Image 1 (tube, rainbow, N blue to C red):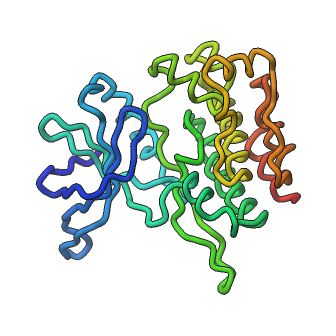
Image 2 (image 1 turned 90 degrees about the vertical axis):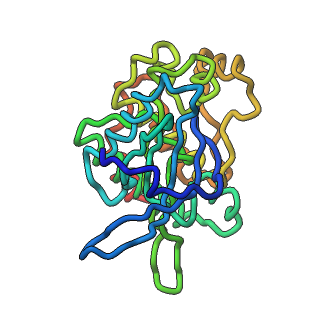
Length: 272
């Protein structure tokens, strides 16, 4: 990871939180190509100081993302570990994360938009699967909208997958249970069961989000009832716009070995 100096970073408005992190919009002063000086908008993810003991996992999450380069993976600029801070510096995306965008724009997102976005996420996950690299936290809140759809120029939306944050293999069990149904049943039973098949299940959950205008599946269920949802082997209800329901359910297969490859997922999406 490239080391960025505290002095070159300006923190601006808070944008929200992640697990044990706070997230800000910021500006990075830098020397760019040809020696030109730039003030670049950046996303600043700050590990809580009370949770400094997660620093290794916090950065490992991003470092994995930066081992491979791909048009659908978020760009990490570097880290700032000056002083007592643990800061991840990433590209800033004007349109924010997908979960918010779906909620705010649900009255003007149709099936073709959802299919295009599903296809791009499937392509990103296929890239990871071919590199045998586990993401571990696929969800709409970890997808960024680079570009809106522009029908007038035929331009589709364009998304990127961001890093998974601190791994489920080190998080407390109550947080894992609160993350049902993105966390797959086998990882609730044993978080060290994290595997490539994990991301197929979470991909299904994320498709359900995309088809549900940003609703959170099972949000009405407390942690105890989410656990019992897995014990009783329930599936999610079909979204009202049900075009992707069968794919969602096929990805959310309680048997990890039966979940379809991302190449088969892509072939399925292209059939619609």
